[PDB]
Amino acid sequence: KPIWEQIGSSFIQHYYQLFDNDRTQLGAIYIDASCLTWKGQQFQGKAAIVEKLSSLPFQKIQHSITAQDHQPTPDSCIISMVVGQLKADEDPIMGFHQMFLLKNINDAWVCTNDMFRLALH
Amino acid sequence: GDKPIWEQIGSSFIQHYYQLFDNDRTQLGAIYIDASCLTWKGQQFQGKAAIVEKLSSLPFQKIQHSITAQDHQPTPDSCIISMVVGQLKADEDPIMGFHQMFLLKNINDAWVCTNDMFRLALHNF
Protein backbone atom coordinates (compact mmCIF):
# COMPACT_ATOMS: atom_id res chain seq x y z
CA LYS A 1 0.00 0.00 0.00
CA PRO A 2 1.15 3.56 -0.78
CA ILE A 3 2.38 5.70 2.12
CA TRP A 4 -0.81 7.80 2.43
CA GLU A 5 -2.98 4.64 2.83
CA GLN A 6 -0.67 3.38 5.56
CA ILE A 7 -0.95 6.69 7.47
CA GLY A 8 -4.70 7.13 6.84
CA SER A 9 -5.58 3.51 7.81
CA SER A 10 -3.60 3.71 11.03
CA PHE A 11 -5.14 7.11 11.88
CA ILE A 12 -8.73 5.78 11.42
CA GLN A 13 -7.93 2.55 13.40
CA HIS A 14 -6.66 4.83 16.21
CA TYR A 15 -9.67 7.20 15.99
CA TYR A 16 -12.36 4.44 16.05
CA GLN A 17 -10.57 2.42 18.77
CA LEU A 18 -10.51 5.53 20.94
CA PHE A 19 -14.12 6.43 20.00
CA ASP A 20 -15.52 2.98 20.92
CA ASN A 21 -13.45 2.45 24.10
CA ASP A 22 -12.50 5.76 25.83
CA ARG A 23 -13.84 8.82 23.99
CA THR A 24 -12.59 11.37 26.57
CA GLN A 25 -9.12 10.44 25.24
CA LEU A 26 -9.98 11.71 21.71
CA GLY A 27 -8.09 15.03 22.38
CA ALA A 28 -4.79 13.33 21.50
CA ILE A 29 -5.55 13.19 17.73
CA TYR A 30 -6.75 16.80 17.45
CA ILE A 31 -4.88 20.11 17.80
CA ASP A 32 -6.14 23.29 19.49
CA ALA A 33 -7.43 24.87 16.24
CA SER A 34 -9.13 21.66 14.95
CA CYS A 35 -12.64 21.99 13.55
CA LEU A 36 -15.50 19.47 13.81
CA THR A 37 -18.78 19.50 11.95
CA TRP A 38 -21.03 16.89 13.66
CA LYS A 39 -24.34 16.35 11.84
CA GLY A 40 -24.28 19.96 10.53
CA GLN A 41 -23.33 21.60 13.88
CA GLN A 42 -19.87 23.13 14.01
CA PHE A 43 -17.65 22.63 17.05
CA GLN A 44 -14.50 24.81 17.03
CA GLY A 45 -11.31 24.06 18.86
CA LYS A 46 -10.11 21.08 20.89
CA ALA A 47 -11.96 21.89 24.13
CA ALA A 48 -15.37 22.15 22.34
CA ILE A 49 -14.71 19.04 20.24
CA VAL A 50 -13.69 16.88 23.22
CA GLU A 51 -16.66 18.17 25.29
CA LYS A 52 -19.15 17.36 22.50
CA LEU A 53 -17.82 13.81 21.84
CA SER A 54 -17.48 12.99 25.56
CA SER A 55 -21.07 14.13 26.26
CA LEU A 56 -22.85 12.13 23.52
CA PRO A 57 -25.70 10.28 25.24
CA PHE A 58 -24.78 6.60 24.71
CA GLN A 59 -22.78 4.33 26.93
CA LYS A 60 -21.54 1.82 24.38
CA ILE A 61 -20.79 2.55 20.74
CA GLN A 62 -19.23 0.32 18.13
CA HIS A 63 -18.29 1.33 14.60
CA SER A 64 -17.55 -0.79 11.62
CA ILE A 65 -15.99 0.57 8.44
CA THR A 66 -17.48 -0.52 5.16
CA ALA A 67 -15.14 1.44 2.88
CA GLN A 68 -12.16 3.76 3.47
CA ASP A 69 -10.53 5.93 0.78
CA HIS A 70 -7.30 7.90 1.33
CA GLN A 71 -5.47 10.58 -0.67
CA PRO A 72 -2.38 12.79 -0.41
CA THR A 73 -2.82 16.54 -1.05
CA PRO A 74 -0.31 18.89 -2.75
CA ASP A 75 0.57 20.66 0.55
CA SER A 76 1.55 17.49 2.46
CA CYS A 77 -1.81 16.60 4.06
CA ILE A 78 -3.81 13.34 3.91
CA ILE A 79 -7.57 13.18 3.31
CA SER A 80 -9.33 10.06 4.67
CA MET A 81 -12.95 9.32 3.79
CA VAL A 82 -14.96 6.54 5.51
CA VAL A 83 -18.36 4.99 5.03
CA GLY A 84 -19.56 2.63 7.74
CA GLN A 85 -22.11 1.43 10.22
CA LEU A 86 -22.36 2.04 13.92
CA LYS A 87 -24.30 0.66 16.81
CA ALA A 88 -24.94 2.65 19.96
CA ASP A 89 -26.33 0.78 22.97
CA GLU A 90 -29.66 -0.80 21.90
CA ASP A 91 -30.55 1.56 19.09
CA PRO A 92 -30.76 0.09 15.62
CA ILE A 93 -27.69 0.03 13.39
CA MET A 94 -27.11 3.29 11.53
CA GLY A 95 -24.98 4.08 8.48
CA PHE A 96 -22.50 6.97 8.71
CA HIS A 97 -20.15 9.09 6.60
CA GLN A 98 -16.98 10.60 8.02
CA MET A 99 -14.10 12.63 6.59
CA PHE A 100 -10.77 13.57 8.12
CA LEU A 101 -8.06 16.03 7.05
CA LEU A 102 -4.72 15.00 8.54
CA LYS A 103 -1.57 17.14 8.84
CA ASN A 104 1.93 16.38 10.04
CA ILE A 105 2.52 18.81 12.93
CA ASN A 106 5.56 18.34 15.18
CA ASP A 107 6.50 15.02 13.53
CA ALA A 108 3.08 13.39 14.21
CA TRP A 109 -0.08 13.11 12.17
CA VAL A 110 -3.03 14.94 13.75
CA CYS A 111 -6.57 15.63 12.56
CA THR A 112 -7.28 19.27 11.75
CA ASN A 113 -10.68 18.94 10.12
CA ASP A 114 -13.43 16.39 10.91
CA MET A 115 -16.87 16.07 9.34
CA PHE A 116 -19.51 13.50 10.40
CA ARG A 117 -22.96 12.74 9.01
CA LEU A 118 -25.42 9.89 9.63
CA ALA A 119 -26.85 8.17 6.55
CA LEU A 120 -30.62 8.70 6.49
CA HIS A 121 -33.14 5.91 5.98
CA GLY B 1 -21.17 39.92 8.60
CA ASP B 2 -23.23 36.75 7.95
CA LYS B 3 -22.01 33.79 5.82
CA PRO B 4 -18.35 32.94 6.09
CA ILE B 5 -16.36 33.09 2.85
CA TRP B 6 -15.55 29.33 2.71
CA GLU B 7 -19.29 28.50 2.85
CA GLN B 8 -19.89 31.03 0.05
CA ILE B 9 -17.11 29.66 -2.16
CA GLY B 10 -17.70 25.99 -1.28
CA SER B 11 -21.46 26.13 -1.96
CA SER B 12 -21.11 27.91 -5.30
CA PHE B 13 -18.30 25.46 -6.26
CA ILE B 14 -20.62 22.47 -5.44
CA GLN B 15 -23.50 23.91 -7.48
CA HIS B 16 -21.21 24.62 -10.45
CA TYR B 17 -19.51 21.17 -10.29
CA TYR B 18 -22.86 19.22 -10.32
CA GLN B 19 -24.36 21.47 -13.04
CA LEU B 20 -21.32 20.74 -15.18
CA PHE B 21 -21.39 17.04 -14.14
CA ASP B 22 -25.10 16.59 -15.05
CA ASN B 23 -25.15 18.65 -18.30
CA ASP B 24 -21.79 18.10 -20.02
CA ARG B 25 -18.98 16.37 -18.14
CA THR B 26 -16.27 17.05 -20.78
CA GLN B 27 -16.31 20.65 -19.45
CA LEU B 28 -15.16 19.39 -16.00
CA GLY B 29 -11.45 19.93 -16.88
CA ALA B 30 -11.68 23.66 -15.99
CA ILE B 31 -12.06 22.95 -12.23
CA TYR B 32 -9.08 20.59 -11.97
CA ILE B 33 -5.39 21.27 -12.46
CA ASP B 34 -2.53 19.02 -13.52
CA ALA B 35 -1.69 18.01 -9.94
CA SER B 36 -5.36 17.14 -9.15
CA CYS B 37 -6.30 13.78 -7.74
CA LEU B 38 -9.53 11.75 -8.18
CA THR B 39 -10.57 8.57 -6.34
CA TRP B 40 -13.71 7.18 -8.03
CA LYS B 41 -15.12 4.16 -6.16
CA GLY B 42 -11.72 3.16 -4.71
CA GLN B 43 -9.66 3.68 -7.90
CA GLN B 44 -7.11 6.51 -7.86
CA PHE B 45 -6.62 8.73 -10.96
CA GLN B 46 -3.65 11.19 -10.86
CA GLY B 47 -3.70 14.33 -13.01
CA LYS B 48 -6.16 16.38 -15.04
CA ALA B 49 -5.96 14.39 -18.29
CA ALA B 50 -6.54 11.02 -16.53
CA ILE B 51 -9.44 12.49 -14.45
CA VAL B 52 -11.22 13.96 -17.45
CA GLU B 53 -10.90 10.73 -19.47
CA LYS B 54 -12.33 8.62 -16.59
CA LEU B 55 -15.31 10.99 -16.07
CA SER B 56 -15.98 11.25 -19.83
CA SER B 57 -15.95 7.44 -20.16
CA LEU B 58 -18.64 6.59 -17.55
CA PRO B 59 -21.42 4.52 -19.15
CA PHE B 60 -24.45 6.70 -18.30
CA GLN B 61 -26.28 8.88 -20.78
CA LYS B 62 -28.30 10.91 -18.28
CA ILE B 63 -27.22 11.75 -14.76
CA GLN B 64 -28.85 13.84 -12.07
CA HIS B 65 -27.46 14.64 -8.68
CA SER B 66 -29.40 15.89 -5.73
CA ILE B 67 -27.67 17.12 -2.61
CA THR B 68 -29.05 16.10 0.77
CA ALA B 69 -26.35 17.80 2.80
CA GLN B 70 -23.18 19.86 2.17
CA ASP B 71 -20.63 20.72 4.89
CA HIS B 72 -17.74 23.23 4.33
CA GLN B 73 -14.70 24.13 6.45
CA PRO B 74 -11.55 26.26 6.07
CA THR B 75 -8.28 24.30 6.39
CA PRO B 76 -5.12 25.63 8.12
CA ASP B 77 -3.22 26.26 4.84
CA SER B 78 -6.06 28.40 3.39
CA CYS B 79 -7.90 25.69 1.48
CA ILE B 80 -11.62 24.94 1.56
CA ILE B 81 -12.66 21.35 2.35
CA SER B 82 -16.19 20.23 1.51
CA MET B 83 -18.23 17.06 2.22
CA VAL B 84 -21.37 16.25 0.25
CA VAL B 85 -23.98 13.53 0.93
CA GLY B 86 -26.74 13.09 -1.65
CA GLN B 87 -28.60 10.91 -4.11
CA LEU B 88 -28.01 10.25 -7.76
CA LYS B 89 -30.22 9.07 -10.53
CA ALA B 90 -28.54 7.77 -13.64
CA ASP B 91 -30.59 6.64 -16.63
CA GLU B 92 -33.17 4.04 -15.48
CA ASP B 93 -31.04 2.68 -12.68
CA PRO B 94 -32.38 2.80 -9.16
CA ILE B 95 -31.64 5.92 -7.12
CA MET B 96 -28.38 5.46 -5.24
CA GLY B 97 -26.89 7.33 -2.29
CA PHE B 98 -23.40 8.80 -2.71
CA HIS B 99 -20.80 10.69 -0.73
CA GLN B 100 -18.25 13.10 -2.22
CA MET B 101 -15.42 15.23 -0.85
CA PHE B 102 -13.69 18.21 -2.52
CA LEU B 103 -10.52 20.03 -1.43
CA LEU B 104 -10.33 23.51 -3.00
CA LYS B 105 -7.33 25.79 -3.41
CA ASN B 106 -7.06 29.34 -4.73
CA ILE B 107 -4.59 29.43 -7.62
CA ASN B 108 -4.31 32.53 -9.88
CA ASP B 109 -7.32 34.27 -8.26
CA ALA B 110 -9.52 31.17 -8.89
CA TRP B 111 -10.64 28.30 -6.69
CA VAL B 112 -9.60 25.00 -8.22
CA CYS B 113 -10.14 21.43 -7.04
CA THR B 114 -6.98 19.61 -6.12
CA ASN B 115 -8.56 16.51 -4.48
CA ASP B 116 -11.86 14.79 -5.31
CA MET B 117 -13.18 11.54 -3.81
CA PHE B 118 -16.46 9.85 -4.75
CA ARG B 119 -18.10 6.69 -3.49
CA LEU B 120 -21.56 5.12 -3.99
CA ALA B 121 -23.52 3.86 -1.00
CA LEU B 122 -24.23 0.18 -1.66
CA HIS B 123 -27.60 -1.40 -0.91
CA ASN B 124 -27.31 -4.07 1.80
CA PHE B 125 -29.23 -7.05 0.34
Image: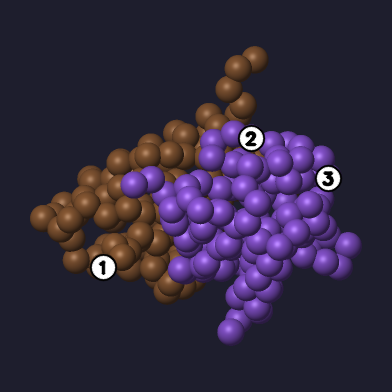
Chain colours: A purple, B brown
- The percent coordinates of residue B60 (x first, y second) are 18, 60
Q: Is residue B60 left or right of residue A81?
A: left
Q: In this view, does B86 lie to the left or right of A60?
A: left
SS for dot 1: loop
Are labels 2 and 1 on one chain? Answer: no
In the current view of this chain or complex, which residue is farthest to the front? A90
- Crowding at dot 1, Cα within 10 Å, few <14 / some 14-19 / many 20+, comes out as few
| Residue beneath the point at 65% across and 51% down | A59
Q: For this rendering, which residue is in front, B8 or B111?
A: B8
In the picture of the structure, the residue carrying the numbered disc 3 is A32
User: Which chain is home to disc 1?
Assistant: B
Q: How far apart are marks 2 and 1 (CA)?
A: 34 Å
Reply above or below: A57 against A73. Answer: above
What mark, if any, has residue B125 been given in the picture? 1
- The percent coordinates of residue A52 (x first, y second) are 70, 40
Q: Distance between the residues labelled 3 and 1?
A: 43 Å
**Among the two numbered marks 2 and 3 on one chain, the one whose residue lies closer to the N terminus:** 3
Quadrant (top left, top right, bottom left, bottom right) of the C terminus of chain B: bottom left
Q: For this rendering, which residue is in front, B73 or B5?
A: B73
| Residue beneath the point at 51% across and 53% down | A90
Q: Is residue B47 left or right of residue A34?
A: left
What mark, if any, has residue A42 been given in the picture? 2
Q: For this rendering, which residue is in front, A38 or A104?
A: A38
| Residue beneath the point at 43% across and 53% down | A92
Reply above or below: B111 against A105. Answer: above
Are labels 2 and 3 on one chain? Answer: yes
| Residue beneath the point at 76% across and 40% down | A51
Question: Of the residues shown, which amino acid type is indicated by label 1?
Answer: Phe
